[PDB]
Each structure stands twice: as C-alpha cells, then as structure tokens.
Length: 144
Length: 19
Image 1: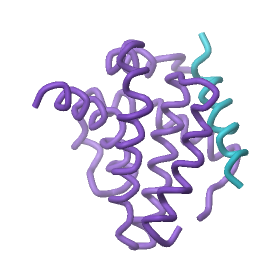
Image 2: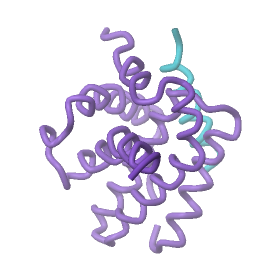
Image 3: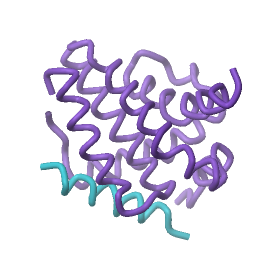
Image 4: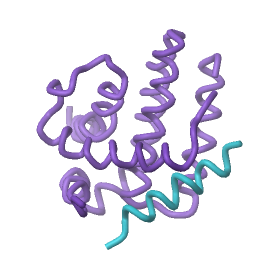
C-alpha cells in the first residue's frame, strides 16, 4: 500500500515482466513501454551469455532455492552494479524457462525466489543509485 | 559448477557497466 507498493512496482517492471516474456506466459506487447526498452539490454545480455556457456540443470522447490541463492549471492558478494542486475534478471529467466519447459510447475518458485532476493538484497542499492530511471538510462548504452 | 557461472555473470555485467 505504501513503500511496499513502490518496491512491488519496481521489481514487477524490472524483473518479473522480462521473465514472463522469456517464458511464453506473456506476449511481447503485454509489456509496459519501460519493459521492451530494457528488454533490449536483457536480451543482449542473454545472447552475450549464450556465447560464453550453456546452462543445464532441478527437481524440487528446495533445489531451486539453494541453487539459485548460491549463484546470485556469489554474484553480489563482491559488489553490486546494474550490469550484474541484468545477469540476475537473465539468470532468473533461464531457470524459469527450464521449469516451464519441464512442465514441473516450479517456475512460480523461481519468480518468487528472485523477487524475494531482489527485494532484500538489491533494492536498497538500486533505489540509492537511480532505481527504475537509471536502469532505463542503463538500457540505452551503445546501439552498435 | 556454480562459482564459475557467477564470475561469468559478473564479468559480463562488468563489461556492460562500462562507460
């Protein structure tokens, strides 16, 4: 209703929306204008990552939490920046895509695990460093 | 593994955070 509503709106726009489009639960033009703009840099991050290596894994809610937590907590132990927030989002989308693929009905667990982490561990950093507007400025970068 | 994926996610994120 208050600060929770702000935090909920930010995470929904920046994280949940892209995962639901990476997952085919939601079409491309179901996205807010803010979302297809930042989709570009998330999409580009995904392709940059697929050059590097491929991901293959998860059978239980318990296994999603430990595997997801382990990676992301190691992703930000060192430092937090908008570039690795992209990787966080992207990584969250790739584990959700795995779930809807296997039709295990665990993608919901992925979204909620990523949401919880971004709220507790990332949102104070992102708010103080420009938040939603900055990630929008971060999306432009070099259009090569 | 998992520790190596992070450093991949890290340095990619680091490369995009440039300039």
